[PDB]
Length: 288
View (tube, rainbow, N blue to C red):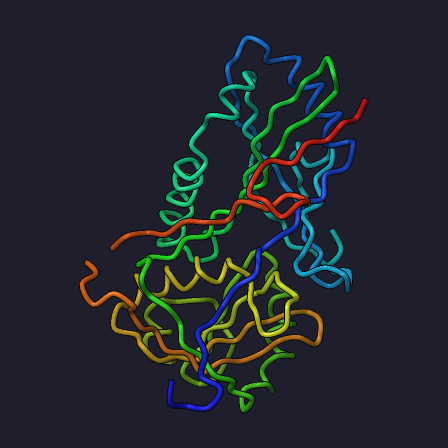
């Protein structure tokens, strides 16, 4: 870099799983109904509380309970997040499943959704195996985060002149609880993402799930991948990372490729949650 404070943007895991015993109790009750199946995929809903993230956290917790299996129809200050649980009834299959291929398939659905509506490119998946005899549960949270093209990086530096917008973005996100992104229109009004407007105005704000200083959620990758698809000629733009704490920040951003011989493109996918030891592997819970 040549500009002071120019850096490549780096990311933090989008969510941290927090499974209550009730989640496993419900999983067990429901598994009893599908013993004849090799595997099942059931939708889940979690409610994110981005206003009350514990100071000890690096990102918003994903609170899974018995209620996560239910259809949610109506909660005070919260963002509904849809996902699913893939339960495998054969432990060997759970173990042997190619996890990168699986997460890549999930990311492809998020991508397909996102290029129609950028607000629909976020999801989570839990894979599980439940030993009902031992009451031991293996699980692994994946959050499909995709970088397409794989070789694009984002160079950024601070843009504090835009800090005034943070309060308005926070409020807009509060009201529009189904939305992950907003933009400025040509007259600096905050409005829903529109790929024809952003091509002109070049200011995008994202509802961030990270609390790490100057390090946005990996979900940012998803939104930026959709942005590149929507506006291929966009190189320089402003990016606001909006948080409900005091940690929002604004960036003067520039797309660049680290591979001059890249096509136009590969999709890099990541997002499996590290376990307690920090390894990329499932978590296991003994509830006996």
